[PDB]
Amino acid sequence: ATKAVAVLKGDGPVQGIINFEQKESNGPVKVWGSIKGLTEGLHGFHVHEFGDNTAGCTSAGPHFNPLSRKHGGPKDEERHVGDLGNVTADKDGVADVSIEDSVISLSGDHSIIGRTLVVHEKADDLGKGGNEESTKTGNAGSRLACGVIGIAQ
Ligand SMILES: [Cu+2]
C-alpha cells in the first residue's frame, strides 16, 4: 500500500531503492527510486513477476503480465504489475526517478512482496521490448538486476 522497498543484487552492482505508494482507491502512486549501475542508460521500467529469487528472477524472464498496462506502459494505465517509472542511468550508473501518474500500480499482479524486479541500466521497454517475443513479454534481463520488490511496511 503505502511504501515499498526494492533490493536488487546482481553480477554487476546494481542497487537502488524504489518506494511506491498505491491503493485500490485509485490515485497516482508517489514513487521514488534511485538506481546505481554499470555505465549505461536505461529506459522504461517493466517488471513482471509473481516472485522468484532475489538474486535473479527466473519467472521474470519470458512471462508477460497483462494486468499491468495491458502491455505494461511506463506511465501505467491500470495496475502496472511491476515498478512503474522511467529511469535513465548515466555512465556512472545513476538513474533519477520519473514518477508517473499511475492508477493502481503495486508491483505484482499475483502479489507484490516477493516479486522480483526486472530492470537494469538498459531499455527495459514495456510494449516494444526488443525482438518479437521480448516485445510481447516486455524486456527482462532476468538476472541483470533483480531482487525482491515489495511493499515493505
Ligand atoms: Cu523488464
Image: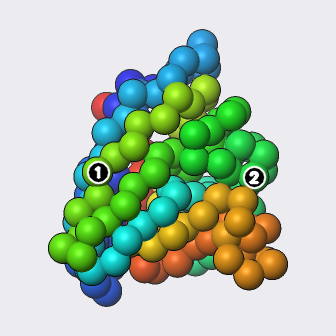
Q: Nearer the viewer, residue 53 or 121?
A: 121
- On screen, residue 102 above or below 67: above
Residue count near mark 1 (Cα–Cα under 10 Å), binned few <14, some 14–19, many ≥20: some
Residue at position x 54%, y 37% in the image: 106
Q: Earlier in the sequence, mark 1 or mark 2?
A: 2
Label 1–label 2 contact, CB within 8 A: no
Q: How many marks?
A: 2
Residue at position x 48%, y 35% in the image: 100
The single residue placed furthest to the left in the displayed view is: 92
**Residue identifier under label 1:** 96
Q: CA distance from mark 1 to mark 2?
A: 23 Å
Q: Quadrant of the C terminus?
A: top left
Q: Is residue 37 left or right of residue 133?
A: left
What kind of residue is marked 1?
Answer: Asp
Q: Is residue 60 left or right of residue 53?
A: right
| Closer to viewer: mark 1 or mark 2 | 1
Q: Is residue 57 visible?
A: no
Residue 114 position within the rendered picture, expressed as x and y whole percent measured from the top left: 47, 54
Q: Quadrant of the N terminus?
A: top left
Residue at position x 52%, y 29% in the image: 101
Residue at position x 68%, y 34% in the image: 77
Q: Nearer the viewer, residue 66 or 122?
A: 122
Answer yes or no: disc 2 within 8 Å of ligand 1: no
The single residue placed furthest to the bottom in the displayed view is: 11
Kindly indicate the quadrant of the structure image that contains residue 47. Answer: bottom right
**Residue identifier under label 2:** 71
For label 1, the SS is strand
Residue count near mark 2 (Cα–Cα under 10 Å), binned few <14, some 14–19, many ≥20: many
Q: Is residue 77 left or right of residue 85?
A: right
Residue 86 position within the rendered picture, expressed as x and y whole percent measured from the top left: 46, 51
Q: Is residue 82 visible?
A: yes
Residue 63 position within the rendered picture, expressed as x and y whole percent measured from the top left: 72, 67
